[PDB]
Length: 497
Ligand SMILES: *[C@@H]1O[C@H](CO)[C@@H](O[C@@H]2O[C@H](CO)[C@@H](O)[C@H](O)[C@H]2NC(C)=O)[C@H](O)[C@H]1NC(C)=O
Ligand SMILES: *[C@@H]1O[C@H](CO)[C@@H](O[C@@H]2O[C@H](CO)[C@@H](O)[C@H](O)[C@H]2NC(C)=O)[C@H](O)[C@H]1NC(C)=O
Ligand SMILES: [Cu+2]
Ligand SMILES: [Cu+2]
Ligand SMILES: [Cu+2]
Image (tube, rainbow, N blue to C red; front, side):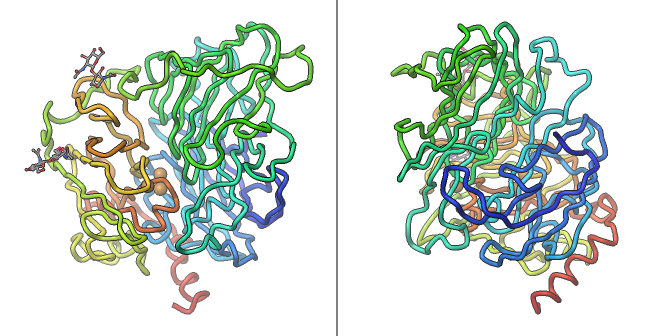
């Protein structure tokens, strides 16, 4: 069952063995991934999060972010620790009470404290559209058509040794998959379809790090949604999906009744499909219960290329059609050295007082805000351009902006900008050396919004800044509930801060 839009959600520790290897985890709703939280566009979500964590090896504090939901007027509910709140302490609960006007699509939720989401606190979040303009393109769209892609580690996130390379031990598709080393024939996920029907597959990367090359043997995939934004139909046979991105695609169950491999190849960790790693099964009703015998092609015919995507609606691009053609044109210097990332020379280290609380307490310029150099003000009602030139180690980096989606005026691996009809999305690969991936948006959402790489290990190592959007109107725009005001006193008392 899906839960929500009004629900409790308990965060617990438990052992799980999604690839046959038992380890403790941090779970929402007792499962990995967590249960789907769902409602309809415009609904009031009230997710009362109960922190029941007791194992300090994965942190007993928590905070949850609702990835891709704009939180307009509810910045306090956004979830990034020390940006919009202090964490919830164990034995306490907190109602994330917000609305989703003007949004409908495929989202997800995850811990936003340290690297805790890697330890298991991740799940889908779907906002259905009763009047979806794409409704006639498919027959089935429900919990059985959500496909999550996850990296899974045998080493606990807090226990990843300083100075050694971090790679995953298994790819999990819908929570199941096989380990790259010491592979055992643990159960694979099965996605079931009926011959002749069409499915809205909601593909969600809940990755802490790798991107995946996703395909389904014998089938192609017609993209209709990108990170919550309806797209024109784009047929592809492979999707490279970066951490935190989402696509909806129509799967036409138009192949012979049978079994077909579902493939998700990460860019790090195990390469290939030996022993059934990196795999799940598409099974038609009436097929024999056995593994597929299909193969991938050597070369895919129609891979997704980001510049091929275009919005379904006439979204355009704000500003003027040239580089720097914005009210506030920015170019960030994104770098890595000696174990830490930096943005414009500053590595992000979370502050003691959340940025939002600093603003509400009267700190009203961004030079006043801690961490020094990590908070950049944005003016209200303005076109913002942010160029994100790649080159920093550990790429390709998927950058994500809270509080907003954005026009992708320039994509990876293509030097040509598009000021006419690029896709809008919320998480974008900044590509490879020499690229100049560039985003644009308008500032109509007062509050401090995190901008960061969504490889969680890189966020932890400092690859982030905060955009303090319309500082002057932040307090009036975002009235805070008493329970939010109680978070930092409770946290600081528990931790002797
Ligand atoms: C990415 O595009 C930005 C503009 O969006 C470029 O920024 C210019 O950089 C030069 C120095 O390299 C400055 O003189 C200009 O003032 C900047 N803004 C302009 C012209 O609008 C940036 O160089 C590009 N980066 C890469 C690596 O291609
Ligand atoms: C590189 O990106 C550019 C800009 O998005 C792409 O150019 C567009 O190509 C389409 C399809 O032929 C044309 O309708 C548009 O007029 C082009 N726009 C611009 C601004 O040139 C281009 O196709 C991409 N390159 C590749 C190889 O996909
Ligand atoms: Cu987010
Ligand atoms: Cu990164
Ligand atoms: Cu985030």
